[PDB]
Image (cartoon, rainbow, N blue to C red):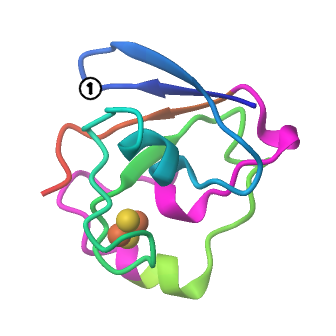
Amino acid sequence: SKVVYVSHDGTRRELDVADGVSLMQAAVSNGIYDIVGDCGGSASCATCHVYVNEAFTDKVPAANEREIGMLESVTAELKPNSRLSCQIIMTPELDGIVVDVPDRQW
Ligand code: FES
């Protein structure tokens, strides 16, 4: 399924992500270095911070308690649509989703 990553400077990178793969896993495995994933995807580092696009902040599953708590550690600006890319799991229903990577993760 399609996922679009928009960097700080507006550069756009589109990837084909399989079911069950997190947006963080797909990013780091494809050279989208704006996303780090320091903790490995267990929601404990906040270095995979991303701003989910408004056309999907409704679609994607709401943030869990652990994510909510770890989000406070993001170094970039925390917004209403700030999510940890490692918590967004790809499915056909998310096809076309767009997320913007913060100016920084640290
Ligand atoms: S990869 Fe560490 S919190 Fe998402």
**Residue 103 visible in the picture:** yes
- How crowded pointer 1 is (Cα within 10 Å; few <14, some 14-19, many 20+) is rated as few
Report the residue marked by disc 1: 8
- Magenta region: which residues? 70-96
Which residue is pictured at 26% across the width and 38% down the height? 34
Which residue is pictured at 43% across the width and 76% down the height? 43
Give the residue type that dot 1 points to: His
- Judged left or right of residue 93, residue 36 is left
Q: Residue furthest left?
A: 106
> Could you say where residue 19 lies in the image, as x and y percent from the top left?
77, 49
Which residue is pictured at 86% across the width and 39% down the height? 92
> Could you say where residue 57 lies in the image, as x and y percent from the top left?
67, 47
- Judged left or right of residue 81, residue 72 is left
Q: Residue furthest top?
A: 11
- Judged left or right of residue 23, residue 1 is right
Q: Is residue 75 magenta?
A: yes
For ligand 1, give the image quadrant. bottom left
- Judged left or right of residue 24, residue 54 is right
Position of the N terminus, as image quadrant, is top right
What element does badge 1 sit on? loop
**Residue 83 visible in the picture:** no
Which residue is pictured at 78% across the width and 40% down the height? 94
